[PDB]
Amino acid sequence: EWELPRLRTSFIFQDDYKAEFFDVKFYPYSPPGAPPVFAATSKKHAVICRLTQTTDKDANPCEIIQLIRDDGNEANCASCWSKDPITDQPLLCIAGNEGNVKVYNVTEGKLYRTLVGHGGGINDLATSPANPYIIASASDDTTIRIWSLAPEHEKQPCVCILGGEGHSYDLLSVAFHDNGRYVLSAGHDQVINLWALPEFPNEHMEIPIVIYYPHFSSSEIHNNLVDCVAFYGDLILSRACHEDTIVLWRIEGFSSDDPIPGPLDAPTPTDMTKQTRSYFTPSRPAMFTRLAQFHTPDCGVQFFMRFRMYHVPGKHPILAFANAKSKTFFWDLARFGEYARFMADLKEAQQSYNGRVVVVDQGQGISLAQAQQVHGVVMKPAWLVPGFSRETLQAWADMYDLSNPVGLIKAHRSLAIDGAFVGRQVGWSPEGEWCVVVGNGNRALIYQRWGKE
Amino acid sequence: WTVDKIASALSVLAEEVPQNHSRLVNFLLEETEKRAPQPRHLSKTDPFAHMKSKAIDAPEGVPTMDVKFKQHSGEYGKSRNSGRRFQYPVVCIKPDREPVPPYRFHHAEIRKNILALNSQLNFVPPRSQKIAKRAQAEYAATLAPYLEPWLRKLNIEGCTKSNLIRFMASDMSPQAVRNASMFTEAWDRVFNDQSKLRRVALRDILMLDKNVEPIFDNKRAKALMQKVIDALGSYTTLGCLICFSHDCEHGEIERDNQKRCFSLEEIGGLMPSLRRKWAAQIEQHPPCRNECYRIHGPPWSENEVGTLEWMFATIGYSQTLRPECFVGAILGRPCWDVHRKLQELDLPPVEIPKQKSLPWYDRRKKQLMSDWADATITHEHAVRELFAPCHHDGPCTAANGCPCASAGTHPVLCERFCLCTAEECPLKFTGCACHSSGKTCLQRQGRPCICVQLNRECDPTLCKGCGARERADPENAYDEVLHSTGCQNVALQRGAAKAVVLGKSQLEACGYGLFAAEDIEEGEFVIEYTGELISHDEGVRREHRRGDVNKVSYLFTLLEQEGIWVDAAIYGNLSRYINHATDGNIMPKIMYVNHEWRIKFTAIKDIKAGEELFFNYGDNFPNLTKKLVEPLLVPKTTQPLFDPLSKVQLLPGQPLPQHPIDDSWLLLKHRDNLQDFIDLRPEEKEFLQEWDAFILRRHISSEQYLPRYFLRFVREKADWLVSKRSRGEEFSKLVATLLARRVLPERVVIEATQVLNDARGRLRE
Ligand SMILES: CC[C@H](C)n1cc(C)c2c(C(=O)NCc3c(C)cc(C)[nH]c3=O)cc(-c3ccc(N4CCNCC4)nc3)cc21
Ligand SMILES: [Zn+2]
Ligand SMILES: [Zn+2]
Ligand SMILES: [Zn+2]
Ligand SMILES: [Zn+2]
Ligand SMILES: [Zn+2]
Ligand SMILES: [Zn+2]
Ligand SMILES: [Zn+2]
Ligand SMILES: [Zn+2]
């Protein structure tokens, strides 16, 4: 359960822009323990594989079950999943450089519908966790559109535009909060915005609702174009070009237990020198707080590279990201606390026992009981590899110490990739045992853990 | 103490900062991990269960693609073979709709031009300093909460936040100031190491103090008559003369975004207008339902006596209006009460040179004669500069420094806001003389219309023969019978545009264009060009930030010499989609409209419904940076048509979408602007914002319509006004200011007295 993935399968899909995989998402609406199925999006194709675990190390766990080509002129780079509201069968939304979302009935290989209205290319798509029929598009036209696939909205499916002056150049990333009413947006203008959506009427909407002001807005978390942003609970993960970090940070005064503010609660830009404004703020405080920076060396000048946190009840949160130099990085978030506990027990035992302290690997056939019988005894997690030397203590701090908000957390697992590879996107299976990294050369890297080989 | 001993102490207290941080980050990670959300909306069945590998084994005419797979094992990710390749058929799905023409930003509609602040150029399609400052600011925010608990822990005499703030602007005990210094440096020794970029001077922490900070927040608003002037200060300073809002689209934005409102203080403040009213009065009813002094005749707060003071001064030497009934309804007092107080109080003395009439202009016949085009620049808007309306004491001459006769290259006429009158000043504008049971104030008229010749629209108040009073009222904008006779030159105040519709332009070069949705005849007003009003440098900054520095930026010149452009990139209306053509069917013109300058389009050919509109862009859109380096229904057309808001395609023949203009975001901005002042008390902001939220929605250009709107406000808010002392008192100052301007007739102060008393008696429940 402390286990981190290993490379199990890779493949190269024939060059179809004569070329990159730009997106990968596992289907999220399958009944528990169903075979995981993901779609990888290239510039012209959606490749849909089932993954099945194998006793045979040479068996190919991957089955390609559907292969769809965008037969129009668009080059795509974004996808998300939804469902038919009547039939419940899977819907794949694909969007690209013409400014249209295609919705595909993938089990039947048919168009479900087209979502038209953006004035420029779409770079990112996200389904609301609260409502599988609500889609958000981020576009070069600098706006976000919220679309609904519910039956009452078929004659006009744009239910909301996030407009105004909060953004002034191409958007690269859009993300939903788990409650479905807070949206993060970010892009080339280096602004990260948090918007509060209204509730949308259960009936036809002649015009979409327009929002002119985000409730939180800052351009100061990063010093460059922001190409990926996400909620982790109510915390925020975000990444910019040139920085080689994924930043964990926090909006001061933001909690999703509080009621949802309406549009006229939003702050307005009354002072044109302020680069951060926020509805949520409580000496003048920060309106945001940098918490931690995961280190992702060697992204170079590459941008449009996305991370994904695996976040599910009763399993460890895992941050995954691949750089621009053939490496995939993992962080187990539960290791941070385990390390804090073990280092707490260590210093508390070095003071109560003058240094007469004995460390012992957990997870063997032992207990801090069988450990105490043999002679202070401190239980060390099995995944903490080397009184300890200084280099060992620095090696442990670098991966696990969360004391410096501008420190650099080294990946807990760094798996090299054969040949040159720039990662574009990472996706996780529902039960967390597969992790698929897609990227240039139409390549997909399939990582596994908890296998059956 | 010693600088090194306290720096030693700070160093050990600093030890809690990273360990608290680790406690905080670790705490939030575990809360988040345990609050992790369960996936929702799962299906009862696996929808892919029935789908096999589509790999081909050793089709026909079906597209095919290859995929080569590799397997990997071990810790190193080593492959177990060179890998196997498979072919798959391809399902080709075409989209059923085409994208709409491209665009940037969300295009929102505004009913009138809005005044834009200047922006900072931060994004373009020294950075070294900007990163440095942000690293420091983030660190100052981290340590700020630690200053005073540390001062507490240290317990150093003279080491108080208040006193470090004193040493920084450098009374403070002798060994206090000694400790002050030793604390300041040492802080710098422990926290402002000039080697590191994550450094912060104690001074940067003290400047975040809630009492210190507003010292640098430059958002400042501003005998018996000195009390009045001061009590009315907020209204005389902020109250717009054009539109009567306290935060509105008028006035001048300076470079640092300080605004000079177009208000009474721009023309001398209260006294020059008020003395003038007193005088006009010198050269010259029913009882209230609250125990009036007509029929008859609890200590007083100084606010209550102030209230009656300014209402008495402002009403002035009136003949059919008196402070009692109105003050009474404002306080909670019977009209005899304030009559008693008034008589108990016993509350300045009041003081025309014949001028050479100008031959190019007769203000009694309302006529321009002779050389007039060569004599004046009143009509030529591209060369005009914006001068505060004259408020001098003399005749308007270069000698009294009258800017109207003298500030420009030629004299301009004095306008409605100049303190001169038509009887004194031969430059005073008096409206037009047109009157006709048919159409009047046209272009190609007996006598011509002086308003048309001056390139202005008619004034509701001064143009009394043409019927401008009614035809410039937006509430009669759709009375076709009214507008079929009378004044034909108030189209912008009428505010009604020809039916138009967004579409894909016919030009293989353009994206969108605008199309006529009804028949338009030559000479008719089509639409106004609205947008954000900006300065020269703001236009330059925006041309950079939009990559224009192949023309991508369009900035309509409104006033060339003054330097105002109209940018409809984001805010404007459908006129922003009108395409260029050397022979267009419409034409723009800049018109003076009640001391606003505005852009109208008039048809120059006959346009039938479904035809596209074009105008010759001309020099209307200069390149600012490069100059500096030197039954209404969707017509049937060939082009697709779009809803301006949703961009859904319109069905030719369907009802023209008429969307109500959404302005809540704009009222918010104006509400927030008044709330930003450190200069205003909560009770002033509360009422000012209430009034502005009402009056802004009415888009007033003319004093003609203020009395009506004022009365609709006293009636919708009468309950609210009586609920709370401060609200009536603040309402009273507004009306004081409006009566000193002679813009509120006596008949509405009385009707407001009755509307208020009825709301107050209604509250006596
Ligand atoms: C580089 C961005 C710059 C800041 N900017 C600002 C705006 C308002 C704007 C627009 C836009 O709002 N237009 C609508 C429109 C108006 C408002 C008026 C008329 C008469 N007609 C119109 O259509 C479009 C584009 C743009 C980008 C790519 C493009 N492509 C053609 C083929 N090459 C690849 C894609 N075309 C247009 C840029 C804009
Ligand atoms: Zn105004
Ligand atoms: Zn009375
Ligand atoms: Zn004058
Ligand atoms: Zn004048
Ligand atoms: Zn004059
Ligand atoms: Zn006339
Ligand atoms: Zn006139
Ligand atoms: Zn007229």
Image (cartoon, rainbow, N blue to C red):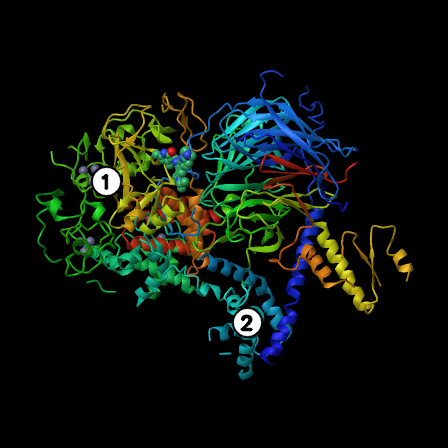
Q: What residue did someone put label 2 on?
A: B188
Q: What residue did someone put label 1 on?
A: B457
The answer to whether residue B674 is left or right of residue B176 is: left
Does A311 sit above or below residue A43?
below
Q: Can you see residue B226?
A: yes
Quadrant of the image occupied by residue A7: top right
> Callout 2 environment at 10 Å: few (<14), some (14 to 19), or many (20+)?
some
Q: Can you see residue B727?
A: no
> Callout 1 environment at 10 Å: few (<14), some (14 to 19), or many (20+)?
many
Residue labelled 1 has its Cβ within 8 Å of some atom of ligand 8: yes
Secondary structure type for disc 1: loop
Front residue of B670 and B95 = B95
* Residue occupying the far top of the picture: B60
Three-letter code, disc 1: Glu
Are dots 1 and 2 in contact, CB under 8 Å? no
Q: Position of residue B457 (x, y in %)?
A: 23, 40
Three-letter code, disc 2: Asp
* Residue occupying the far front of the picture: B82
Q: Position of residue B335 (x, y in %)?
A: 38, 55
Residue under the point 29% across and 31% down: B614
Secondary structure type for disc 2: helix
Task: Say which quadrant the N terminus of chain B sits in.
Answer: bottom right
Which chain letter goes with mark 2?
B
Mark 1 vs mark 2, CA separation in Å: 65 Å
The answer to whether residue B498 is left or right of residue A267 is: left
For marks 1 and 2, give the one nearer the viewer.
2
Front residue of B295 and A129 = A129
Does B347 sit above or below residue B514?
below
Q: Position of residue A113 (x, y in %)?
A: 54, 25
Does B132 sit above or below residue A236?
below
The answer to whether residue B146 is left or right of residue B423 is: right
* Residue occupying the far bottom of the picture: B174
